[PDB]
Amino acid sequence: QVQLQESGGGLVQPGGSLRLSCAASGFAFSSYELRWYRQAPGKQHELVAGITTGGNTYYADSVKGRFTISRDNAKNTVYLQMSNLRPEDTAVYACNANWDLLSDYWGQGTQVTVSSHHHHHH
Amino acid sequence: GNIFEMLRIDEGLRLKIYKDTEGYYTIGIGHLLTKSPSLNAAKSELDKAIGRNTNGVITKDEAEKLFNQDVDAAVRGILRNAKLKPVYDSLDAVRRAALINMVFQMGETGVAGFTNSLRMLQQKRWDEAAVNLAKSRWYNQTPNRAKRVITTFRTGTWDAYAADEVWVVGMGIVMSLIVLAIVFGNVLVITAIAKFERLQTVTNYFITSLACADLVMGLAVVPFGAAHILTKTWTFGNFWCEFWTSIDVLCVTASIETLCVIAVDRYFAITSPFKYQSLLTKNKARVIILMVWIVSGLTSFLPIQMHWYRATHQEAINCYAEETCCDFFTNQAYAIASSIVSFYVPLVIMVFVYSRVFQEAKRQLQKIDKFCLKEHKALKTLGIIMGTFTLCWLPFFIVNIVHVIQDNLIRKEVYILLNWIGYVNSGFNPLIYCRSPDFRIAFQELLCL
Ligand SMILES: OCc1cc([C@@H](O)CNCCCCCCOCCCCc2ccccc2)ccc1O
Ligand SMILES: CCCCCCCC/C=C\CCCCCCCC(=O)OC[C@H](O)CO
Ligand SMILES: CCCCCCCC/C=C\CCCCCCCC(=O)O
Ligand SMILES: [Mg+2]
Ligand code: NI
Ligand code: NI
Ligand code: NI
């Protein structure tokens, strides 16, 4: 069937950088709009970034200038390069391809945790 | 005889007492019972005319029996009239029937009043009496019928009554197209999803259920429904009638409910997308469609085969017992019970969850001004879904509720029409829920074979 698998999340120092990969298989990738959503614990889910078929990218006001979404149709993969990370950016990031109301597919979502005391057990 | 066919498509046929254009109690093929507004007087005249207790309802044989009497009583009334007889003798076989028609409608002493046009008729100056008859109350009261009789008078042909055959064979054509569209549409859909594993998603598993119900409808319900209408009769058993209508209710219930399941499926895929693939599993999916058909079975085959649906009025009792009658008479209870369970409850759910989707789209539409393709295409699809769905089934299920609340409101023909408007929705569904680029590819491949 349709499949979206994220990879590249995990831990990262505040101010650090991560690159999220979203592999797609099972549909006509090239003619699909791609978006990155996230959801902080105990909060409503929000849109991070999004790229159209033409290549037009748009971002949230909070991650504008720091994050950069790009897509590779040759490999059916959309990326979310995110630098200068913050403790607020700690959330579950999900990949999303969309054609219409019914052709709306989501990924399992990957966890990105931003803190300074990583594996420092105080 | 052509006079018999002429009057059949002028008076139609109704097995229950009704009121004609003048508001007089009529029954069968235009048999005036009484000019009194008393139903009891009408019902008494019907009993005397037939020779039994009728309860206001007769049969098709009793209808043709009264019909042949009324025709004969009209001819006798002309021959006995000293002002009508020379005209009748003067006219040809076709034009004779036209004169019989008027007398059948207005009586012998009523037609005799047309002194000027009767003269022009005997003088065989047709075009004169043609415009002379149009200047009468008979023309103003019944414009459509008078034009047909006058035309028959001035031409001496049956061209004025040739329209009935055209609309029938024309309706037979459009019915064939509907049947073809539904079958070709849903077969192509079910085949595509089954053959290609990439299309087999949770959402598309519901569409298979929908396309299945829509397929069975286009194979079983609609074709036998077209024959029942065109032939104006039911050439199968009472068993097959009770089996056919079961498949009707079953498929409609399944089709509409599956549409509701799809709606709730998108509700979870939009409002809580991070939990969507956890809430709705492939396993839970087939559990849902199992319940849908289980429910649909309990609204169709169970109440119908057990005769729980059956109404109690005389016209229904005669219909159930007649091996050539397959009219869908239902009691008030089953009607509103099956209506809410196979339409209204899905409707209120569908309106609710799509209202929420409308909000979520508009909410995101407020955040960014451009590149909102996802939300725009969602709203457009959202309109087509609720548009074509409600426009197809709401009018039917409105008049379905009305006709079991207050009778003599919803005609037979309009119940059929609005029900067939619901039928074509099965043909529209593959045009709505299978627009994805992967469906288009799967379709261009199966058709290129
Ligand atoms: O029971 C409501 C209901 C109805 C349906 C419909 O699809 C049922 N379609 C039945 C088609 C067969 C109709 C045969 C001719 O019936 C003539 C009309 C009888 C009812 C009637 C009688 C007089 C005036 C108005 C209406 C589906 C599901 C439902 O729950
Ligand atoms: C439309 C038939 C209504 C029947 C009863 C429904 C009750 C309300 C539930 C859903 C309505 C969803 C409304 C969807 C409106 C779509 C608006 C539209 O056409 O969008 C144009 C496009 O966004 C420009 O770029
Ligand atoms: C457990 C959920 C069941 C869901 C299916 C419900 C189906 C309801 C359909 C109609 C029930 C039968 C109605 C017959 C009314 C009988 C009363 C009467 O004879 O006047
Ligand atoms: Mg019958
Ligand atoms: Ni530390
Ligand atoms: Ni540790
Ligand atoms: Ni039975």
Image (spheres, coloured by chain):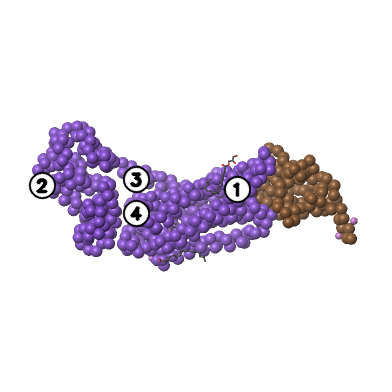
Check contact, mark 1 vs mark 2: CB within 8 A.
no
Q: Chain of mark 1?
A: B
Whichever of callouts 2 and 4 sits on the residue coming sooner in the sequence is 2
Task: Return the mark for residue B358.
Answer: 1
Q: Which residue is mark 4?
A: B408
Nearer the viewer's eye, disc 1 or disc 2? 1
Find out if the beta carbon at label 1 lies less than 8 Å from the nearest ligand 2 atom.
yes
Q: Along the horizontal axis of the image, is A49 left or right of B178?
A: right
Amino acid type at image mark 3: Val
Q: Along the horizontal axis of the image, is B101 left or right of B235?
A: left
Q: Nearer the viewer, residue B15 or B395?
A: B395
Write the residue at 75% across / 53% down. Answer: A40
Quick check: B412 above or below B150?
Answer: below
Instruction: Give the color of chain B as drawn.
Output: purple
Nearer the viewer's eye, disc 3 or disc 4? 4
Task: Return the mark for residue B168.
Answer: 3
Q: Along the horizontal axis of the image, is B128 left or right of A8?
A: left
What is the CA distance from the residue labelled 3 to the residue labelled 4? 26 Å
Instruction: Give the color of chain A as drawn.
Output: brown
Q: Along the horizontal axis of the image, is A83 left or right of B342?
A: right
The verdict on a common chain for dots 2 and 3 is: yes
Amino acid type at image mark 4: Asn
**Could you classify mark 2 by the number of other residues whose Cα lies within 10 Å: few (under 14), some (14-19), or many (20 or more)?**
few
**Could you classify mark 1 by the number of other residues whose Cα lies within 10 Å: few (under 14), some (14-19), or many (20 or more)?**
some
